[PDB]
């Protein structure tokens, strides 16, 4: 599935709510694009492939 969440810069992590309403965390990639560039930026998670892209 594809979820949209919000990321935090320092921890470089995406937080999204799954369909049960549970906050779930998945680290952004560390190097260049796909890393979180500002607190509360959008991030898109693909739970089929365990992949995230952070803004």
Image (cartoon, rainbow, N blue to C red):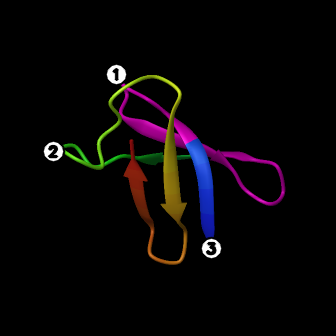
Quadrant assignment for the N terminus: bottom right
CA distance separating discs 3 and 2: 24 Å
Side of 30 relative to 54 (left or right)? left
Image: 47 above or below 9: below
Q: How many labels does the image show?
A: 3
The residue carrying mark 1 is 10
Question: Mark number for residue 18?
Answer: none
Of the image marks 3 and 1, the number of the one nearer the N terminus: 3
Residue 47, position in %: x, y?
55, 69
Picture residue at 15% right of the left edge, 44% below the top = 31
Element type at marker 1? Answer: loop
Element type at marker 3? Answer: loop
Of the image marks 2 and 1, the number of the one nearer the N terminus: 1
Quadrant assignment for the C terminus: top left
The residue carrying mark 3 is 1
CA distance separating discs 2 and 1: 13 Å
Side of 10 relative to 5 (left or right)? left
Task: Tell me where the magenta segment starts and ends, as one range.
Answer: 6-23
Question: Mark number for residue 31?
Answer: 2
């Amino acid at each position: 599935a594809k979820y949209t969440g919000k990321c935090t810069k320092s921890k470089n992590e995406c937080k999204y709510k799954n369909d049960a309403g549970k906050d779930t965390f998945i680290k952004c990639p560390k190097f260049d694009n796909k890393k979180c560039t500002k607190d509360n930026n959008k991030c898109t998670v693909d739970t089929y492939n365990n992949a995230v892209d952070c803004d």
